[PDB]
Image (cartoon, coloured by chain):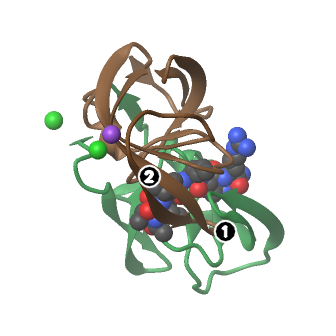
Chain colours: A brown, B green
Amino acid sequence: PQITLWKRPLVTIKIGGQLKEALLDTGADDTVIEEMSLPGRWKPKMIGGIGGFIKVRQYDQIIIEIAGHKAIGTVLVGPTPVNVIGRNLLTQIGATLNF
Amino acid sequence: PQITLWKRPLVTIKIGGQLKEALLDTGADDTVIEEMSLPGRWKPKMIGGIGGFIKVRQYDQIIIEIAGHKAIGTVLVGPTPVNVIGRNLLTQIGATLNF
Ligand SMILES: *O[C@H](C)[C@H](NC(C)=O)C(=O)N[C@H](C(=O)N[C@@H](CCCC)CN[C@@H](CCCC)C(=O)N[C@@H](CCC(N)=O)C(=O)N[C@@H](CCCNC(N)=[NH2+])C(N)=O)[C@@H](C)CC
Ligand SMILES: [Cl-]
Ligand SMILES: [Cl-]
Ligand SMILES: [Cl-]
Ligand code: NA
């Protein structure tokens, strides 16, 4: 699709068998999802932005479907106020900024 | 241009006659820049990010160039970790997200 930016660019994702809403965030290096179970091993990470830092769990090789487009990559899980799809998965669905 | 997301989407901006670097950020409602002097009166605003909330100074109808495109609009100034160009100005330069 072509997504205009008059409103927040929210899409449906499927992760871990669950449907969620998430924000497409070109300003995020990483993908960060609210608390949920994911398979495999994890390691802790601290990630920051406006307001400071939160602690998350890093899971690798997670398959996600983003507005219908499958991608695989690292997903961070923790107390984020908003589910965010960051660049590590936006690249995989071929997302670009155009002007 | 067409900007891919393998690296951070950093562009040069011009504000107050000065060149700065900023992040094109579809996940930001607003444009937030690090401490600098801007003309006129400001109004208070609270904004949120991944770590919580911060207070910023809201300046309206500020002239700002983004990657060579002229915009005039609201700029927030405060303790953001990075300069961010949000949707308020991304819409003025005609930016879309495409996949
Ligand atoms: O981790 C890397 C190194 C990097 N961190 C830093 C410190 O650079 C990073 O990628 N951080 C990510 C991040 O927070 N990126 C932000 C830009 C760069 C840091 C400032 C942009 N993220 C968005 C979405 C965050 C959602 C939790 C963001 O902060 N949006 C704000 C911007 C402020 C503004 N007023 O526009 C935002 O839109 N805030 C509005 C509220 C939105 C509330 N939405 C809901 N649903 N409640 C607002 N009006 O205040 C993070 C994500 C780590 C990878
Ligand atoms: Cl990844
Ligand atoms: Cl590409
Ligand atoms: Cl504006
Ligand atoms: Na894994």
Q: Are marks 1 and 2 in contact (CB under 8 Å)?
A: no
Q: Is residue A76 left or right of residue A79?
A: left
User: Residue at 32% across / 61% down in the picture?
Assistant: B10
Q: Chain of mark 1?
A: A
Quadrant in which residue A43 is drawn: bottom left
Front-lying residue, B37 or A88: A88
List x then y, in percent, for residue A33.
55, 40
Is ligand 1 less than 8 Å from the beta carbon at label 2? yes
Badge number at residue A51: 1
List x then y, in percent, for residue B13.
39, 67
Q: Regarding mark 2 in the picture, which secondary structure is present there? A: loop
N-terminal of the pair, mark 1 or mark 2, is: 2
Q: Chain of mark 2?
A: A
Q: Is residue B1 visible?
A: no
Q: Which residue is mark 2?
A: A28
Quadrant in which residue B55 is drawn: bottom right
User: How many other residues sit within 10 Å of disc 2, few (<14), some (14-19) or many (≥20)?
Assistant: many
User: How many other residues sit within 10 Å of disc 1, few (<14), some (14-19) or many (≥20)?
Assistant: some
**Amino acid type indicated by mark 1:** Gly
Is ligand 1 less than 8 Å from the beta carbon at label 1? no
Is residue B59 placed above or below A44 in the rendered structure? below
**Amino acid type indicated by mark 2:** Ala
Name the quadrant where ligand 1 sits. bottom right
Check the picture and name the quadrant holding the C terminus of chain A: top left
Front-lying residue, A73 or A85: A73
